[PDB]
Length: 138
Length: 138
Ligand SMILES: [Zn+2]
Ligand SMILES: [Zn+2]
Image (cartoon, rainbow over all chains, first blue to last red; front, top):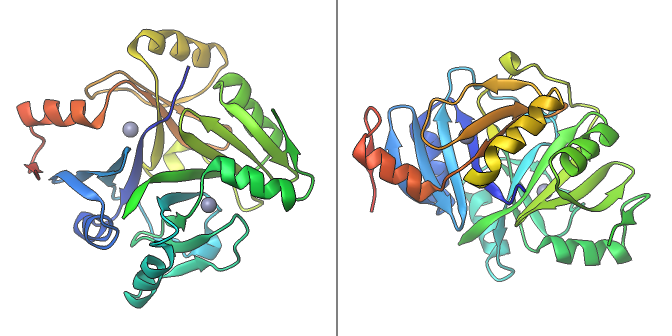
């Protein structure tokens, strides 16, 4: 069977500002970089940044809801979100429609998120406050 | 500070064919569905499919290299690739890198991959044969 995300590859227009964002600002571990990409890790996540001349910025209102959420503890969530805000990182969504989340953009307009909680916790919360028409499968 | 990938959300244009693709063809576990989305899991990956009228079925030549790779064992790789081929699933790239990889498209054109191998394995191969401009960080 398939089991797990092996890696997430993000196309980037400029490699150095992207590496700086993920390593310096988000605190991910940089393992290697080369003329056309970089490999970082975030816990078990393998992140590849790939220099792509085809990557364009799109303002968030003109891209779809595809997005990438990173786990953070309840104790660190608010202060890290506030640090991103204070550093001028743009926000793309304010309404918390899926629990405790902060929604921010990377330098290339990729839609990112900080989230507190697992899938099991989300399902348990949704049993009490379900999305419209929600059905649960055991 | 960040501990890993919390969830991957893919915007979809039609919920039913996307659920069929990820649950039935790819074998992910469906945990819940609502009028505008679904939650699935694939190993430790929490996948959300989100119905979005902004999502377009996008040919691969019209999107950048951003993509999502799922882990599969070497032993299972060939039969799973054959399953995708039997289902008529389009391929967007041929593999030219270390470790088995199959590059395929979802119903909306999201770029997916099956990959055999870890970040550690990739780094070991790169240390032996570094890419142009490659620098490592310990
Ligand atoms: Zn999210
Ligand atoms: Zn890949």
